[PDB]
Image 1 (cartoon, rainbow, N blue to C red):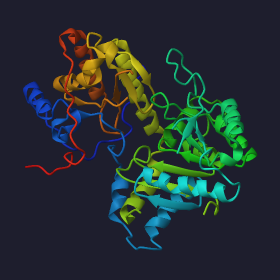
Image 2 (image 1 turned 120 degrees about the vertical axis):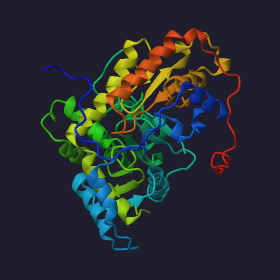
Image 3 (image 1 turned 90 degrees about the vertical axis):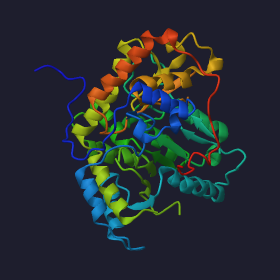
Image 4 (image 1 turned 45 degrees about the horizontal axis):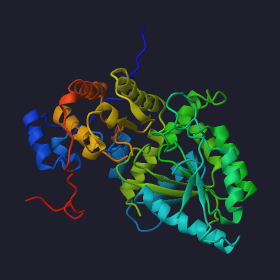
Length: 420
């Protein structure tokens, strides 16, 4: 009868990966052997791993089944055609280049689109500038409501159309190799982009004839927010909003490691023949993942848990500098005000969080921030309350927590280095 802030899982758990519960004595000894650097910890010793949401998520039954029927043929693989058919039936793009990683797609379209405008419109490599809502030099054009956490706004990842149009005039249209639209945006822990904004952005792109690359790891989540907020599309499905959305970009480049729900993969796809690396089982798995990732019941649950964790930390007095859809940045300085910036307040908070709850977080972020990310369909509400209770414990005992003079950062080659 009542309302649930944390939605029930619209799925049944099928396969699980056991994780051992540890004593504080075990963790305190483990965090020491790692040199007070949770990044070096063994996966077995981490109870809740918030390090990254990329490739660490779960899969569905149909996705696992897809791995079983592959076609490993070097060419004319039915597994490739199945993937292409999904890209075509979803985004509307009939040309598909599978890549190992999302980063692999960038290695392709960037040098290609640059050389293209160099041949045609005579682009200058010294004066060249690329534009985006948020991220060779690239310039971010974003609305001022984006980074303001004091106020809530329906779409904070929108382009600044005035700033976009003005910026093109400054550098000149011949010098702009492309426009990268990120959905959801990468700004402020992530924020959705409206369909009206993209449409408007694309009209500007044709005026100067600039190719628009849609960078979407999160395309499914972005479509959900358009259905949830933008009034016109309220009765549209997720598939429909996605099909409409990609009319307003020329090509897409993405990591499949997020909303496509796969451990590894990437895509570079185009709706035109212009402007011109995966095993069969993996392509088959991704072709299923793109559909399962767009599930309406699933997207509501995913987005609800993230919001549940953010709302949870807020109520216990933990302030976030930025908290979006795909990430939350906790302010370690404000949580540990007695620790000088010299002693690495963020790295210190990470260790204490592991000592207490066995939770792993990363320091990357003048301000000292601790980033939190949630792997998809991995952890439950109980884990969320466990993370909140940990921050609650750290806040009360905060005074007795000490900083760190030493941060242990060995070479990149140990880091690897097989065990003894």
